[PDB]
Image (cartoon, rainbow, N blue to C red; front, side):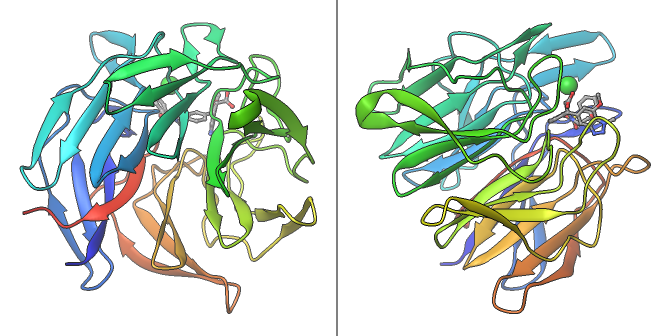
Amino acid sequence: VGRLIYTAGGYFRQSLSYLEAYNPSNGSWLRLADLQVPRSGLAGCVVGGLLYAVGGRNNSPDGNTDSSALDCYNPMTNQWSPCASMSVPRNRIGVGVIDGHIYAVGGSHGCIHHSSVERYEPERDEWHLVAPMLTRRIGVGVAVLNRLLYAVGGFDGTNRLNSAECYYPERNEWRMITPMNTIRSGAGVCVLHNCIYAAGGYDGQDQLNSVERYDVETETWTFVAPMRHHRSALGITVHQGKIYVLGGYDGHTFLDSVECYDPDSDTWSEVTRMTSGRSGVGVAVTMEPC
Ligand SMILES: COc1cc([C@@H](CC(=O)O)c2ccc(C)c(CN3CCOc4ccccc4S3(=O)=O)c2)cc2nnn(C)c12
Ligand SMILES: [Cl-]
């Protein structure tokens, strides 16, 4: 059975509870069980075929509540189940999975911009802090390559960042890597082949269409073809060797545009529209439901 791209949550006028799944094999969207609590600025990931929604904030007519929540969606049952909450609320979070564990990276709680990082063990339903990043980062992009965790760009409370760093699990240690050529907060960050991609983002002045990638072997960042749309706070994932970017904000519109990147041709193509424009979604890929 094929795999779908799931988008959870996001923001349009207020934080959203939508869970919808796109099937690249046939172009279809399915609306699935809503999140129990609306949330924007969350991240999605998958472990053991389960979809997890991590952190965010409920920006609603009746207030703004940063989320420490971890919730688990089972495609086999179409149900959300609460898991243990994180140590702290983390809005505009990034996450990465290594060796079946979820790393929650940075994000904000009110005016607190976190450098802290914590790790979730599904088999124990427990979170534990690990070493903090060298830098406070909200709107941080996170990717995993070769069982190493990367935190890329973001906003430290004062400046948006071109900096990036790498976490070495067996040393419980963060070290800076080569900075990007572009300042990016709320970029989409993912991995494809031996490269970390950083797509779009916000630099304090503009939403960006540029895309660059870090080759871990050469330790250098290189720009590739820009996206068709400028976008910050986009969702990003990889499905069958291609990068998909979903939604985001372009300084004018909350985008419904979904674009995909073919690395072999260095081209971006429009592939579908989300059912409604939105930014700050969580995105991941897993099996079709039921
Ligand atoms: C301060 O303005 C901005 C901040 C960010 C950054 C944070 C920063 O650099 O200060 C950012 C990064 C990541 C995420 C998820 C967000 C929040 N989302 C985008 C903004 O839209 C809203 C608005 C209200 C609630 C939630 C959202 S969001 O879609 O979750 C911001 C991105 C922007 N893009 N355009 N503008 C005007 C931006
Ligand atoms: Cl926000």
